[PDB]
Length: 176
Image (cartoon, rainbow, N blue to C red; front, side, top):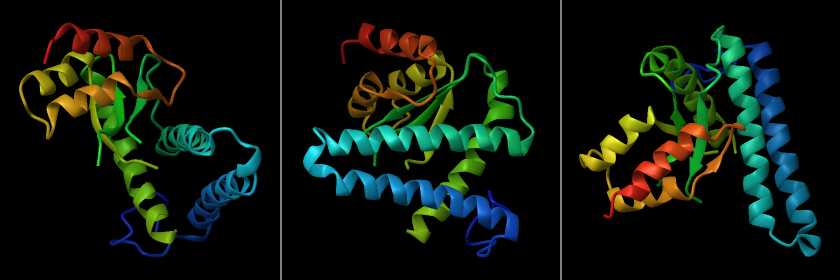
């Protein structure tokens, strides 16, 4: 059972996958614990929880690129839509990048499913700003206006914004 296998296919992790699994579980448990315990001295505990989850997921993303031996493209972005919703969405610069990046997020999706069971949003969409705008323009998505809105109000997981702004500016330009 490797770290990024489907739970239903490989229910037990190998010894090494298990240690890494437990390391993520423990960051999650600790994050949850500290937020709840300090709730009386925290202004916005749910925002703190979200912000911590974005950091853990960012870490998990770097870890998955490394474990799969894939170089993360430098212009690639990951944004969180929502609070289902559109969830994490991956914006690449070129459509060529999708082939190499998509299997890494699929791998992460599997690991996130496992973590859910043992107790973060899945990544659902991946594309260029053009691609994703087009899926909204052409009605390929359940609940277009609310998907659109969630993109407008998404928060960045990686410290990259340029493509995200192209997508938002494209959305903003279309009236409904």
